Amino acid sequence: YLSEQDFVSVFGITRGQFAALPGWKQLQMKKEKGLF
Image (tube, rainbow, N blue to C red):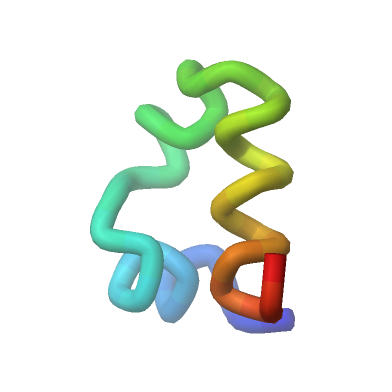
């Protein structure tokens, strides 16, 4: 619910590194910005 760049600003990572991180850590971060 935030542009891939705005995401990087809020997430503190890159689109590249995120796509490399485990699918769980990915979904975890998405949900964490929400409420887990």
